[PDB]
Amino acid sequence: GKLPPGPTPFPIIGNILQIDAKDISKSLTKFSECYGPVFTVYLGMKPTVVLHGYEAVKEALVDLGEEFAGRGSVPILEKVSKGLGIAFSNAKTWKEMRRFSLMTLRNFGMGKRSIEDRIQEEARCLVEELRKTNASPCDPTFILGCAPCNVICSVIFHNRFDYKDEEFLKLMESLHENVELLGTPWLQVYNNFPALLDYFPGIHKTLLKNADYIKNFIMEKVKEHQKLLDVNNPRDFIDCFLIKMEQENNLEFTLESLVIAVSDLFGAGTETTSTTLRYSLLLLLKHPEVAARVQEEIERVIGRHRSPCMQDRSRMPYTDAVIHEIQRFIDLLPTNLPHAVTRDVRFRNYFIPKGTDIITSLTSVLHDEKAFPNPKVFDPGHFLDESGNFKKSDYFMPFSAGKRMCVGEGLARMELFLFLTSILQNFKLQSLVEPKDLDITAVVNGFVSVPPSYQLCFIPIH
Ligand code: HEM
Ligand SMILES: O=C(O)Cc1ccccc1Nc1c(Cl)cccc1Cl
């Protein structure tokens, strides 16, 4: 019996007034200092168990993986998914979509053209459009959003779009707008106070219009794929899904579920990778010696006359340590994505009833002071041994862990490695201000820690 301890909840509104509206993780870490690694908080009337620290997070997500494999409250967004898709689905529907997606999203899961090849083509397109900035000051937000989005287009539709393509920009504008409107760390909130929906219908209204533009953009391509389907040679996510439908026995596979599953991948993989890439460049501007050392490794291992490839990563410990350090340092999703227990569970000396929402503090793992000495300081050394070789850490958990762990983790890491090295191989980064005046403090917008706005010049290396 009994839920974990926690701050005394004021009637109806819960612990809201005790949580920093700008930085919930910071609040969760303060609560943990006086309630321990496992505590409860109220985002309204319903209790939410918070897991803080590597041991608690790992014990639940990994050791008790099935119990914590549920997708917690994610209002509106969960509703547009209609219990289908991957991110907000649960039980059998989730299991089948996730299994299908993992098998399909392998490097060579969709024919002879690997996911790596697709990312390499995009890395070249990214370098080309950066050349078009002609070494003038520019905000990289747009182009850095296009590349990741195009990578997903390539793996889903087997097609990429020009960075000036109307529908594509629209897709990104529809994706962006939708994630912005439906942005908040709590998330559990829209499943609580209905009066707020009417006070601020703006956030909830355009979603049907744009999330439908997304669903419509996708459905349109699906129809095109059905006419060109080759059962012996599927070349993208859609074909593989269409084949799974043709033969089948699976009622979980419909054109409706395909559209939603594709919406999820786009939603989960576009903004995260884009933000990480944008934050990467900022950190390189902030610590130019890091950028210089990565370039030294690029020249020595890859050289100047060929595109970087995944095989290069194992031979580039410094660059790998830098990519790991960027993800750990930026802590993209401070509180992960909301989980929920799939059944009554006795976690340690506490009892957690089925359906209870769970929040895991990834910030507490990624910034553990013992696993990463001086955790608030950017230092690739956190992933380097005394001999300059790459050093793994069980605390490197930016993609989460367990049964719900990021489905596109492999794809994301390839994108970071190939885009960053292709960028540093072809350009020197020049900031308008000195590193000492460069703001690198993140501001959590929705679920994501985004870097402050900045501009830079991409000076071609020749
Ligand atoms: C730097 C980029 C990325 C980061 C940091 C990231 C991080 C994460 C995290 C922390 C979660 C939540 C895990 C949980 O519930 O415990 C997640 C979920 C997910 N991610 Fe990513 N992600 C990134 C890129 C990608 C990409 C490129 C794709 C798409 C191909 C994608 C697809 C997914 C999906 C489908 C889920 C939901 C999985 C499920 O509920 O079973 N992610 N991601
Ligand atoms: O699913 C979407 O349409 C995007 C979306 C909206 C709200 C909350 C989460 C997500 N996707 C998502 C996922 Cl699945 C993991 C990490 C980060 C993000 Cl933004």
Image (cartoon, rainbow, N blue to C red):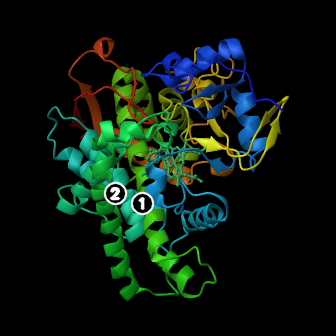
Look at the numbered disc 1 and say if its residue's Cβ is closer than 8 Å to ligand 2. yes
Classed neighbour count for the residue bearing mark 1: other residues with Cα under 10 Å, few (<14), some (14–19), many (≥20): many
For this rendering, which residue is in front, 141 or 63?
Answer: 63
Q: Quadrant of the N terminus?
A: top right
Q: Which residue is mark 1?
A: 263
Task: Out of 133 and 181, give the one closest to the viewer.
Answer: 181
* Residue 445 location (% of width, % of height): 38, 32
143 vs 81, left or right, is: left
Residue at 62 percent across and 43 percent down: it is 339
Tell me whether circle 2 and circle 1 mark residues in contact (CB < 8 Å). yes
Residue 406's place in the image compared with 223, above or below, is above
C-alpha distance separating marks 2 and 1? 8 Å
- Of the pair 167 and 417, the residue shown nearer to us: 167
Mark 2 C-beta closer than 8 Å to ligand 2: yes
| Label 2: element kind | helix
Picture quarter containing residue 31? top right
**Would residue 303 be visible to someone looking at this image?**
no
**Type of residue at label 2?**
Ala
Dot 2 crowding, Cα within 10 Å, few <14, some 14–19, many 20+: many
377 sits left or right of 35 in the view = left
The residue where tag 2 is placed is 211
